[PDB]
Image (cartoon, rainbow, N blue to C red):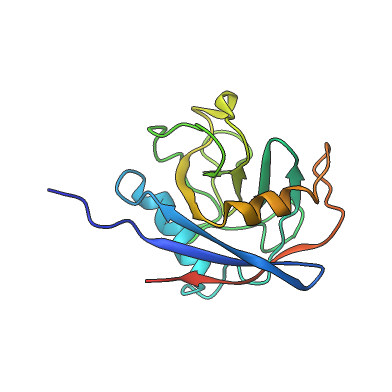
Length: 168
């Protein structure tokens, strides 16, 4: 069969509570359905929990912006829609360049809710982080976010997902 149109999610980002702009993502539901569905549902909040009001805890210039720890706000928390953790679905897609959306994890088969947005090609992550989407619009907003990170990931201003959901 021919694929359905892949879903699209938005984040509205704020910096110290001041609006910055919107980033929207294509989710590769065609190729990585279970992992796309988790991120989609966490973005709408439809299971009773999710990304709205969470922070980007770890940002490294030249490398990636990381968020999705909506329970502990520091990289030690988060949960999936399936349970605390779920398996690596597949490694079909690779970390090819800026904009790629991929799962953060704590080793093999430990996906929760944490994710990162690449700002460069990061091929050393191929085969151990599941790639499941890409920025489709607002890569410039990710580049603005990026400036507020540092080599050790600590942010110099508070970067938050003020609002998020699905646009048709």
